[PDB]
Image (cartoon, rainbow over all chains, first blue to last red):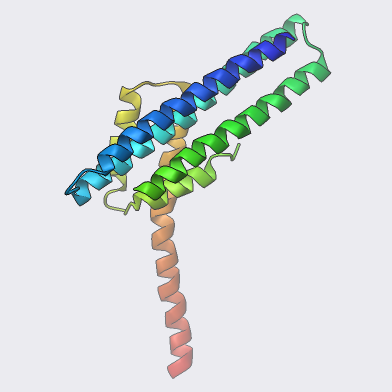
Length: 114
Length: 80
């Protein structure tokens, strides 16, 4: 039950990251609707998108790292056995695959708008 | 640890960088990213982007030269 709490910390943290990405991609799409948008300003929107998408990747990679270290502490103390520990990393990977799908779907629909 | 290659690739195809502007585009990306915050994952993601941007720019030039070389050799076997 204690690893279940650590997984809830990672799930909420990865979802705030994906929402931070969502809200900034909306802000970039509004500025892409500007009238008389120059080709240079369109490039500056592309660069700002890559910055946001990289931040979303690295911050999810940051939440995953902290969750694995919080479980490494539990394993060394002895609160989780090998079966419970290996179940943690298995369900931590599905949350990671899920955050990746949502992150990619937001960037994919934004690219299609621009 | 390959989960981000499809995303890295789609980003590079959206940006459409060249050999001349890739480093300028990269330094602007790197600066805006680290000015908003630096952590382990962002340094890994940026370096991951950097390396693949280099491969994207230079594989573009590689397939071109291979096309010229191959088309030349078969052209000489065609007319001569």
